[PDB]
Length: 34
Length: 34
Length: 125
Length: 125
Image 1: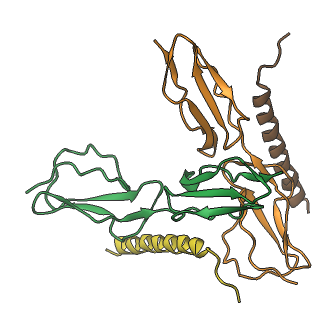
Image 2 (image 1 turned 90 degrees about the horizontal axis):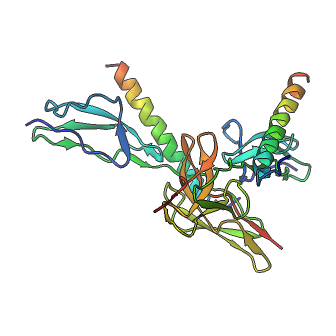
Image 3 (image 1 turned 135 degrees about the horizontal axis):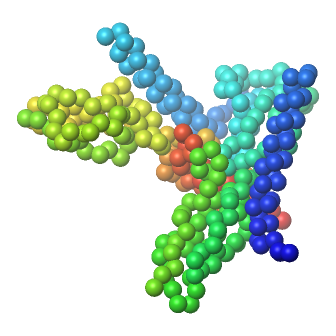
């Protein structure tokens, strides 16, 4: 029941940081598994 | 066969940092050896 | 067919300070990591020497972004572009007040992440 | 004949926070280390109390220097003095482009070394 304030920005910050965290998970798995 | 680009600057940066590293090596040897 | 030393990147630096032997076997891959102020945005963080003796790579880092610094009591915090590394926000005070402190602040490198250059000002009187 | 407390130095700070007993035996030597933004440039990093009750020392730190940040696509990176701590570089865009971002950047303290205050701008359109 609440419009997201211009905290769309924080949300964008967090998603980009979670993507980055995924990329690490990716090549970390991909390395040792190869 | 390549003129050093204005990367004389990086080269200067690295040499100063290697001198510093030498100074540490100097007094570290000079300390315990005394 | 082979590569000279790699271009310096504005957003990333090579892992492992190696002698950087001024020449590299075609097909060599070098591992990079994001500079402070930057976060990873691609799976492959490498430059590779291709068949034409050239280093190839994509922009695998993006700007980090600062926390929103919150509200300015009796004032306003104005986003001008975004809250990314390098961007600036502006501060202002409502009609009955004087701004004490800085009118701007900038998302900059702090610790091992990113943060605001100037503290929020106060709106007073 | 003896020394009062040592002068504060702009380029270095004393190792060991000790009570800094306001007076010091003549001939005492205090150990210093380089401040952030500064690198060691002499073997002796000390102030010593001489016979005349005065602290003596030479400038044993110099500025750290930033990596060259690389090229500006479709633009130019202009060194104005050098790339040392405190110095500024300037950015410009070639005839057919608009500069988006900062026109300058400054070598500043970052992490435990030194780095560029602002990210490279883009040259666009």
